[PDB]
Image: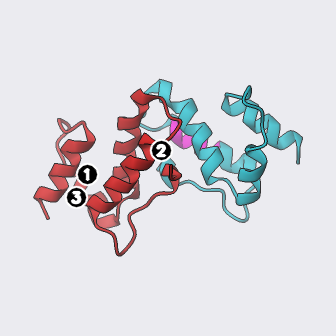
Chain colours: A red, B cyan
Amino acid sequence: AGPWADIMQGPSESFVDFANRLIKAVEGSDLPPSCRAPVIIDCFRQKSQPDIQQLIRTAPSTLTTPGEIIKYVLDRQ
Amino acid sequence: AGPWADIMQGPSESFVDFANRLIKAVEGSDLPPSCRAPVIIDCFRQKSQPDIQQLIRTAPSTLTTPGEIIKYVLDRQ
């Protein structure tokens, strides 16, 4: 699919649009299935727009899946 | 350490300098130990300068570790 490691949230892209693009690229990648979720998490933390990076880092340590982080961000927009 | 998913080979950087920076950042990351090598491999394929990306994709399917890919590239420079 798309080169997942190149994906960053662009200035006309919402967080969720970026999350969806990123996840699709990771799912289509050659990565071991068990690495998908931690790579997605790291890319949300590092590759979203800076304001979103700053919101994600306020999330509790108990939020450990991509879906939990997505709900955390969208519920605060 | 450094945000590994942001790392790309810059125009004044050699391939090996980029590989070393990338690997250090991945080693310092929160990634599961078993995901380090496949993430490194993917980042070499996607985040090096375009001419290097094109050289890496000529490598045999038998080269499966970061070190094998590093030797493949450096031995051809």
**Measured from the top left, where is residue A42 in percent x and y?**
38, 45
**Measured from the top left, where is residue B56 in percent x and y?**
74, 44
**Amino acid type for the residue under numbered disc 1:** Arg
In the rendered image, which residue does mark 3 sit on? Answer: A55
**Measured from the top left, where is residue A39 in percent x and y?**
41, 40
Point 32% across, 54% down: residue: A19
In the rendered image, which residue does mark 1 sit on? Answer: A57
- Tell me whether circle 1 and circle 3 mark residues in contact (CB < 8 Å): yes
SS label for mark 2: loop
Q: Report the span colored magenta.
A: B20-26
For residue B54, above or below residue A68? below
The 10 Å Cα crowd at callout 2, few under 14, some 14 to 19, many 20 or more, is: few
Query: Of the residues tagged 1 and 2, which is closer to the observer?
Result: 1
- Residue A34 lies in quadrant: top left
For residue B43, above or below residue A12? above
The 10 Å Cα crowd at callout 3, few under 14, some 14 to 19, many 20 or more, is: some
